[PDB]
Length: 104
Image 1: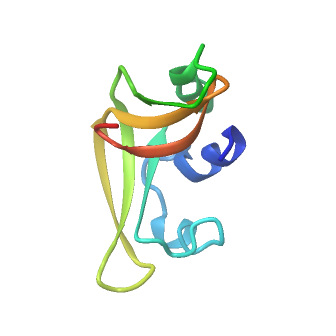
Image 2: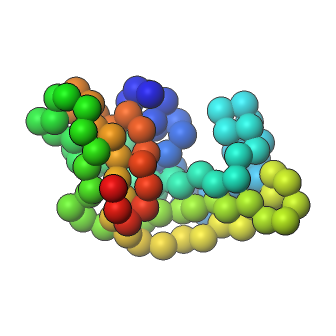
């Protein structure tokens, strides 16, 4: 919804995200999938520099991604690591929602 929340929901400081612990918290409520971007915050904020009105943007560079995808057991996930571009909603020069991997 905003840049503080986007960092908490979609940026990770570790590539090997502990999906079963983090996606069990209220922020994620055992949802089926959540993609995290392995980077310190500023290079991710920079994707949106200059973009004021809300607009979805496909990154121009590929980033390390860590995806938590639910298994057949609720709230237990398999982590998949990949490198790809992704689409975010940029608003007032910061990412505020994660749209999807690979395309807008």
